[PDB]
Length: 125
Length: 119
Picture (spheres, rainbow over the protein chains, first blue to last red):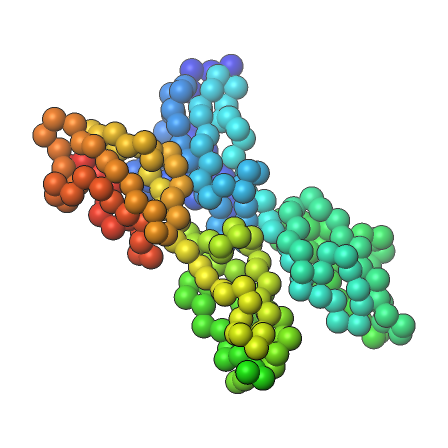
């Protein structure tokens, strides 16, 4: 427990009025900040601005910017996830057409921080 | 019409933009909006189809406007995200104004019509 929170470090995040605060500042309990996520990232509630409050236990809710993953279709393949936007942590299945394959030793392709774990592409090799 | 013109989306980004003239009917594109802008359904990627009546749904990227509070003032819109076309009222304390005795501000394409600040 503490009387303060450290300034929030949010990966892929932007604070409202950022340029007005210092990164080593001690933020008192009860203080309220708002964060947004960079293009291609989203907050847990999908709200453009998310309120975060300094508590004795740290920032509440925990600030987080999750990667959005998408593909419109799969050339020489199919997926129920075609044209659907997925969140970081989601797994998608892709079935390739005859003579094509999704070369990876995993049954599912994951949406990770950097994007798709494996490209959503069926190859002729 | 047998085709649609290539879509010009202000503050928009097409999926596989750096890959693509007249577009035939039935063709499907996906668009996203730049940071601070949003599609009408709020979806990150929006499917648009070329029809005999043009692009369906009509592609659009609307500005999002926000302020957490008003220093030396008040607003029912404090901590609320507003969409392009919305109007917001701000009441300033004792001897303060919003550039200047304007009282009401609106969310426009460039952002807030007047900064939400009581000076």
